Image (cartoon, rainbow, N blue to C red):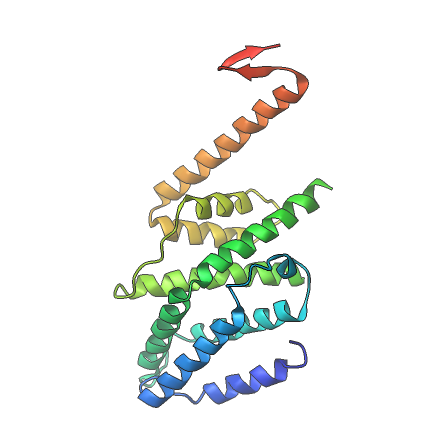
Length: 227
């Protein structure tokens, strides 16, 4: 990744001249996105190698940095019809990414780093990796929200569960704010986001009390306390 950083920088300079309105440019960009997605290797069951620092992980980190640069210039501000090209590129990128199920891979990598955080607390490459793997689903969902014609990604309850668990970590000074804003955007209303967060916090504190009394000897048997 480090030695190929100049390479994808050159790719970025080459793509800065691409116009999303032309069919040839859009097709070439879509092919490049599909090739990068296939390079991501979400089908790999070898998640254990994703936790350790490796060349493949750094290459993937550079890949999402390049993709974030691509979708970070979608501001209609001072754009000579560029706004339209940026919107088309954003929509095509979101469709290609979501249709490939990289979101499930995001869930797997998040739950893998959750084990790392659990192990480290009880006994800045990581920060950048976590920020990118949280920003990519955030940006994808934002783009799909801006374009209702793209089918919405399906988020079951587990995603909220680990996102809340990550929120319980007090080692996140600002990205915690970003995750909170992400969740209130996902719910769409502050009421539901706060309701889920409070419910998880209460459930976690309650099981904490339960197990703390279990270990001491106050046992909850059939909802009856036995000392």
